[PDB]
Image 1: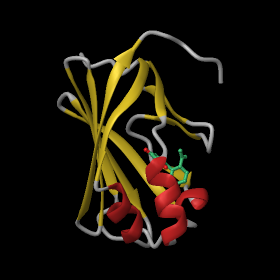
Image 2 (image 1 turned 90 degrees about the vertical axis):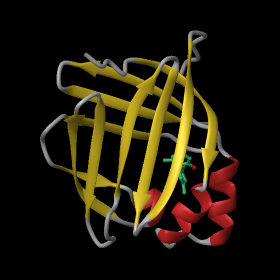
Image 3 (image 1 turned 120 degrees about the vertical axis):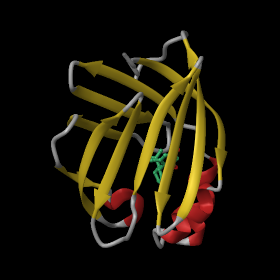
Image 4 (image 1 turned 180 degrees about the vertical axis):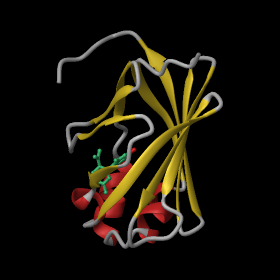
Length: 139
Ligand SMILES: C=C(C)[C@@H]1CCC(C)=C[C@H]1c1c(C)cc(O)cc1O
């Protein structure tokens, strides 16, 4: 039984600028965005999952029910919205973001004290890893 609940600090973020370039994000914002090291605050409450991606530059909040398609507003990231479904795939969480772009989604799992997050679009792959932390900040 995987439970993603916790607070997590970014350790690595690989190939994020190419991921954003594939989303047609402009180069100035790609640089700004790749300097950011957001935290993740996750509360898993039955099939109700809240994933808060937190930084001083911006927060992006996901709040959904596993297995239920919903409209995800990503216009602050790439000026697009998607019809998104998050599903359990073994011990992994699989997200498919249907919309203008082909093959858009991500995959999340836990290894030890690491939260692993692979995000993808148009065959471009960005891999992030976060470490579980215990010192909390208000937000
Ligand atoms: C909402 C935030 C913090 C920013 C907002 C601007 C862009 C273009 C991406 C977002 C982002 C996300 C979603 C995740 C991430 O690891 C790094 C980022 O920069």
